[PDB]
Image (spheres, rainbow over the protein chains, first blue to last red):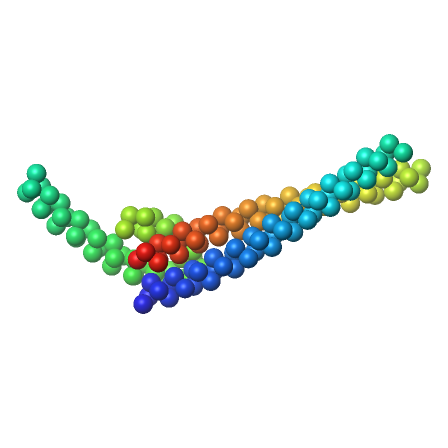
Length: 48
Length: 48
Length: 48
């Protein structure tokens, strides 16, 4: 019973961590794409 | 080889019962946030 | 001169964005490591 309660708490923590990884990773990918677009714009603007 | 095995089976049975008893007391004493980061508990689960 | 000033402001914004991305990426990596440790602990608890 003690092990089962600890396991349930661990499972909840793991699920929250996985959700954070899915969210933080998605945010990082979006930021990287935006940064690449900004860099291309700067490269074009600099040439002009 | 038989006699050594029988002595090994007795030894292993005493070590297993110590590990189970060590796990129950370690889980109760350790906090739910500490259990996830506790190195001793991760090592203990591998040994078992 | 106006174009150069705008380019400099854009570059400063890009550097700030890169720093935010770097720290955000390191936080995401730490979260992923914590999630993996939690998953290993959960697997051990389930086996027990």
